[PDB]
Image 1 (cartoon, each protein chain N blue to C red):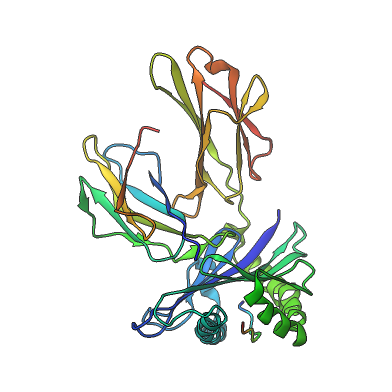
Image 2 (cartoon, rainbow over the protein chains, first blue to last red):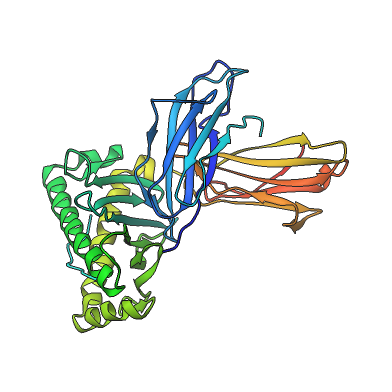
Length: 100
Length: 9
Length: 275
């Protein structure tokens, strides 16, 4: 049984602009097996209106999923993606970095 | 369109 | 350009929790257009792209029947592979299947695929000549011998070279406004001081379709890979894709570096330089 740990990217659909409606994305890829827990966080708290893509996989058989939610960024709100998978000893949190 | 071929491992 | 149609099937056993989970998705190029989920309420193949919704009830009935047949065979496959590998009924295991076809810019057949994985590793795969199989290990030799004596590959050759091509053409035509579009990347470069000594240059490509793209850094016109970082191409969520590539450079030497962007929607490759 090949296990592979998820790669995680957190980013917005459109260039972020404060006060402007947008989508927050958490893209998990390259992982195996397919069971995975993914949450989107606003100031550490779990957002409830999150949708995700249908499970699919790449040429090397590793799975990928997009989780996403509508959001309007501000100057001071912090967003993040929390991911749990059998290859992790504890959930991994990746903060959203607009300034890239 | 999906295939209809019977394929069993 | 070239195009493809692909179907991806994931089957996961759930010991003590009833039937195995089964998910099927279908793609034209980088656009998903159908899905089926064994745990969903409808128990039907469902549309996931606007252009496929025009297909009438005979289409959806036929695809639903075939995807349920695929689900029944994968249910048995899980039990079959557990035996080949002498595994207990206690653990969860994953079977994956992919098949489909690629065509060239004239939309004629280029390559067909039909392959399986078990718990994340190759199990068996149809070879490019569409006559023979690659068995990944000793257990898969059993399947290969059975499929060879039954001429399984010859029947699949007909689907991959026939039905698959014909319906890929039909989808490409019915979905022409989106499937045949080529959205060139929108690009820009950012600059961040890491300290007073070095800076990160980041080359961005946004809202492009299809996913295929090449971002490369050059220094003085020569390809540069040291001190670079490149992320996986990622979906924007609106049907387009995003990617960036970065290089860390000595401060005062930013002007030596160029980012080069290759994409099928560009009439010419782009060259970006800082400011």
